[PDB]
Amino acid sequence: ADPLTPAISDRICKHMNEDHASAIALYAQVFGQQTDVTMAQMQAIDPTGMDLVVESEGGSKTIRIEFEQPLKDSEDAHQVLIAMAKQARSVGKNS
Amino acid sequence: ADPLTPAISDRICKHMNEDHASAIALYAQVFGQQTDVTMAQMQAIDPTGMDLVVESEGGSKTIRIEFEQPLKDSEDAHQVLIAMAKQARSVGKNS
Ligand code: HEM
Image 1 (cartoon, rainbow over the protein chains, first blue to last red):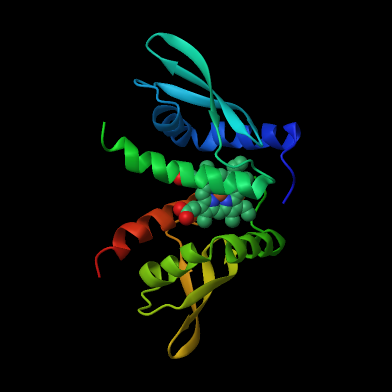
Image 2 (tube, rainbow over the protein chains, first blue to last red):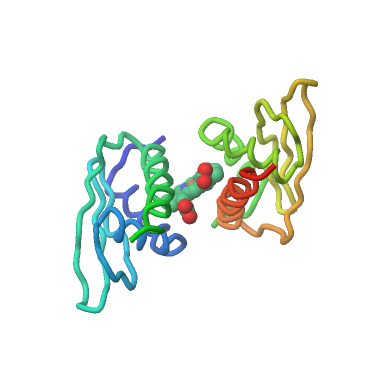
């Protein structure tokens, strides 16, 4: 796969924001430890983490989630976004 | 997104077979109604369905799963592959 350039990041974030916004809000809630998330957007994803813009009652906040293991290409990014969505759905059941 | 040409199909199937083989076996079990699936591969995906090659004890069999609604582009393909994986994991619990 292609390495995680800012160009590739932009395209990943664009597609997540348009077609996977529910998953991003799950990331913000479970991995970002944010309580009453209204919506969340991905601003960037890079080898070591992702930057989320998170909306709630108190307005907007930017947070960073750091990955346990650095991403080496867009396939690593795919696998982590899949795994994080599954893990967040499991955790979000119990609050 | 790009329309579902055989070229795009080839690339989707290639990536599913290399990085999502577990999901394909779930498709074969739940949507293909195949019992003791050893492994499954995607041979083609087109606007109306997907062709799976499915290995079991009795050897190899090709099956077709037809989509309720035809796919119009690669994003539709993405959404159906995601949904089918989630649905198969739910069903596969109860046998
Ligand atoms: C050849 C291209 C692609 C294929 C074949 C593909 C296939 C899949 C499959 C099978 C899943 C379900 C995984 C599972 O539940 O086991 C999935 C999930 C996902 N993919 Fe892709 N994908 C592709 C490209 C992309 C791209 C370009 C992005 C983002 C920029 C992306 C983002 C995601 C996300 C976020 C999920 C999880 C969605 C959710 O949990 O609701 N995928 N993909």
